[PDB]
Image (cartoon, rainbow, N blue to C red):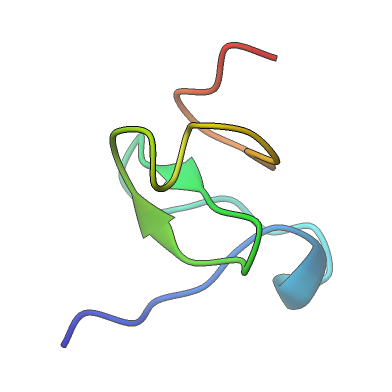
Amino acid sequence: AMDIKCGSQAGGKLCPNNLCCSQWGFCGLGSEFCGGGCQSGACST
């Protein structure tokens, strides 16, 4: 599956597209990526 990483896991790199960097460092959207612990991208906080 798609498994590109970013954030704390990548040592402070962003997603290539505007995706939410999850808790686990992977890019995506919705409550599973942006919903709490969102490191970079389309995050609320």
